[PDB]
Length: 207
Length: 207
Ligand SMILES: CCN(CC)C(=O)c1ccc(O)c(OC)c1
Ligand SMILES: CCN(CC)C(=O)c1ccc(O)c(OC)c1
Image: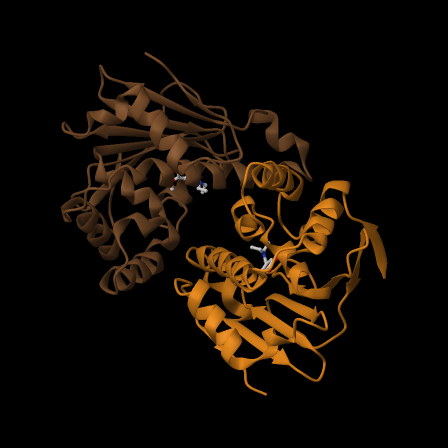
């Protein structure tokens, strides 16, 4: 298990997300679904000139898996996935510069819901989750598990768990007062409201 | 000079853009600026683990260059640029699937301004231009010039013109009745309206 420190600006972004009074929390799902869409676009583009890219899995889609027992909402995609380097480098984002722009925007009247426009939408997972676990598999690497409960550090380990084939799995360990996001009609409402133009199937699992 | 046929679905997207009565043409600039932002994000991300990626040019920005003599509006960025393969493969887009989703959306009430959400925003250049020339330079290839006046075909040639260092240059040969997009206050208005959260400098050249 390797423990790393977040870059200062990312710890601050996470602190802002966690600490700010801000009711419109539901947007975390749209931001995660959108990152999944972007990863799927990437593998699909690569497959256009190299069909073998899809050897690790031909279907391009997203599953939403609520689990009330464990209190987790899981967002799985079969997109391009991430290498160990992508994971350590702020999950494939340009987070330092994105955080800088987001902060300026907030100072000038933007609100937290606009986070995705600064390319750090992943971190909005902290609006609802106390701990976030990311399992990922890229064609060019082995499966890894990234994890953080914020607090300025994250871990990375080689994942021994069930093999994924290819893609990214975001496991949200939901805060005690955010269990509405495990409820079927609430998830369906949010998907329909914010993710109506996502070009891949989104399957909501039932329990 | 190599001449290629557009895939059928792209020729149809272009025909739709060109033929539909649709007044809100100004959005082409926001879509091009946004593609440039995405290319810049890409090179910046690569530079995070490999500083030499920026050997071909350290500054990450966008220039807007109107030229009333030639009737061209040029959008230059110093982003990641495109290889010959990217160019032939619909300028690095997943255009067939993106066109499919855009068409469905239009049929269900979307309008042309939402084109960028389907990842084929580049083609909105045809709302204002009769011919579009794209000059591009990727670290992994030499400089190329892609060109199309629609009509179902595009060309690709190795570019002999002034060397770019790295990035993408979109030269819009504007339609005779679209010269307002060469006017300073009109360009400035559009940038301010639609591109206020682009995290790179956008320099509007004067003539
Ligand atoms: C670098 C590839 N990538 C992003 C396009 C993913 O696999 C990915 C998918 C979903 C996410 O929520 C995510 O969080 C950042 C990353
Ligand atoms: C594949 C890299 N890329 C797109 C991210 C560009 O260089 C690029 C930049 C501006 C554009 O208008 C464009 O048109 C599609 C492409």
